[PDB]
Length: 133
Length: 133
Image (cartoon, rainbow over all chains, first blue to last red; front, side, top):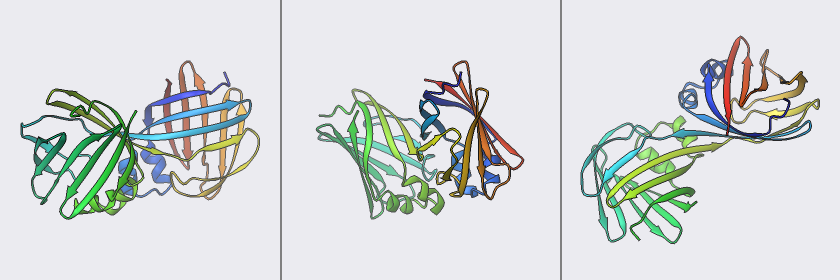
C-alpha cells in the first residue's frame, strides 16, 4: 500500500549515532538524541503529505511515601545522589533533597485543574504549571 | 485537595535555565532541555506516590507533494538548507535531499502494520521501524 496515513510509534532506531555524526551533529546533542523515541503523525491525501513528528524521552520513575526519606539519583538531570523527604504542609507537597546543593527541593500543589510545581536550588526558583488532561 | 492523581500536561516552565545552571547541567544539555514540555502521570494511593514523567520535543512539520521539489531547513537536526524531491518507486517513498552532504536522503514504506524509514548520509544508513498505533 501507498497509504502511509496514521500515527506511528517508533519501536527501533539503528545507527542513529552514525547518521547524526555524518551530519556533524555535536557530541552532546547526539548523546541525548540516541535516547529518544519518535511518534510520527502522517496526514496523507493523494500525493500531498503532512508529517508531524514528536520526540520523547522517558524520565525515570519516582516512587515515594510521604514521611519516608528515600535515596534519589537525579539521573534525568545532574545525576547526583540526594536523600529526599516529602511531607505535607496543608495541601502542599513539600520535598527537601538533602545533599551537596543547598536549598534543593520542590513544592507541588493543585489549584483548580492546574498542578503547580516550584523547584528550588540555591537562589534559583523554577515555576512549572501543568494542566489536567 | 491532596489528590494529585492524574495525567498532567506542562503548560508553563519559568526559569528552568537558571535552575539547571544551579545544578551545573552543561550548556549543550540546557539548550535542548528548555525546549521540552513534560507530561506527568501521578498514581497516588494515600501517601504512596508513583510519578512517571516524559519529556517531549515537537519537531518541525514537513509538508510536501510527491514530485514537487521543495526547500527544507533541517532545524531539528543539523540546521542545513536542502532541496528535497520525493518520488514513488512502487510503494516506496524516496527522498533525495540535494545539498552539501553527498547521498543524503531517505526511503519510507509500509509492510503490514509497520512503517520502515531508512535515512542515509554519506556511507551511513540509519534504519527506523514504527508500529501503527
